[PDB]
Amino acid sequence: NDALHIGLPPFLVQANNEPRVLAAPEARMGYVLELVRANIAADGGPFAAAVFERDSGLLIAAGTARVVPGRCSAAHAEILALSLAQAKLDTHDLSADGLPACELVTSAEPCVMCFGAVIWSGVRSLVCAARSDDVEAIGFDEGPRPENWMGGLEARGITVTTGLLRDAACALLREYNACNGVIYNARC
Amino acid sequence: MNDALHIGLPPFLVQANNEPRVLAAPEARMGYVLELVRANIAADGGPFAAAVFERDSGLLIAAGTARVVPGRCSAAHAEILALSLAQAKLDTHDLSADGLPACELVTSAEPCVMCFGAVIWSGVRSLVCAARSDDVEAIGFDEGPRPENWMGGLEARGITVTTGLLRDAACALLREYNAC
Ligand SMILES: Nc1nc(O)c2[nH]nnc2n1
Ligand SMILES: Nc1nc(O)c2[nH]nnc2n1
Ligand SMILES: [Zn+2]
Ligand SMILES: [Zn+2]
Image 1: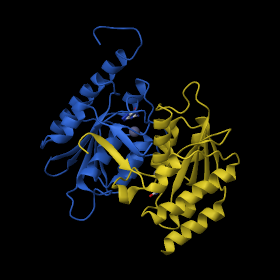
Image 2: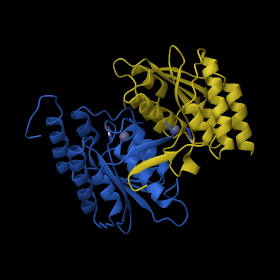
Image 3: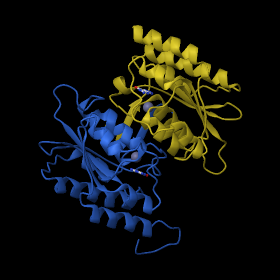
Image 4: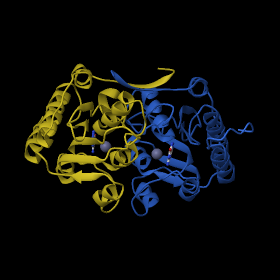
């Protein structure tokens, strides 16, 4: 017990190693939804997120839910993405002087933990696919965020957009739920 | 690292996570957590520490401190480190898993909104705090927008909350830090 060490599965190493620029919001979210499918095939939850330079679309880092495989309840996709972006740029603050403005693109609206992390991270933009109710409907709790948490973010200069590629994101939620049972199903 | 999120720990904190320690009384637990605050300040970190203990025995399971700046990670609050290292040691992402003893997070101050969430997902059954939210805010650390009645929120999820335990001793270390 010498470090907090959350191992990344190969696909997520690959994501974090390959340079990649995606200009349009849909292109960014498209990529994030590819990572959700790959994470569900690597024994993780149906959640992914990536940090992008807001104005160039350069991918800085990506993360996925590794709570179960990584034995770590803090290892939400958003935490991983934000933290790996910080390690890559060698700073705890993604708004530090001389950094480009960063945006977090996430497959679902953040839970209350991740809401706080977004606030501390220095990102200036949050872009979500699935809504909070979508996530809760398949048994993933978002927990008690403050009243008007979106407004809370905007008051901090963090822009919020939600519902982007929401249909595809919901299809991935439903796919994970249908394959999260103990009875073997070869189609899973 | 290409292949992991890795937040290294300073020597005092590695030692705290790998030395046997059983602290029965709540204040003995909190006292050790305040020792960790001081050691962390001397190791270039913020004035925050926390530890996970088996609730009834007071066996220390893991400890964490603020490593935000030297770790280049805004999520590296003392509470996130303590909860995560406890889960790693007990080989589970859920500290309420069947057959595990009830776990308690003992913290130098009341949790920020992020840590409040972390506490809810961790599986701990008890939160014990020293310094108040107002005390942390009064030396320039933001707690962020937590929901109204965040304590009732934790209690409704089966997490008993205690606050103000060795508050004054904790406040002295906060004021020392602020002043330097
Ligand atoms: N609510 C929620 N729950 C999970 O398990 C997650 N993992 N990554 N983001 C997540 N969000
Ligand atoms: N509010 C707050 N701020 C920090 O920087 C911390 N580090 N550990 N707990 C913390 N809590
Ligand atoms: Zn989350
Ligand atoms: Zn915190």
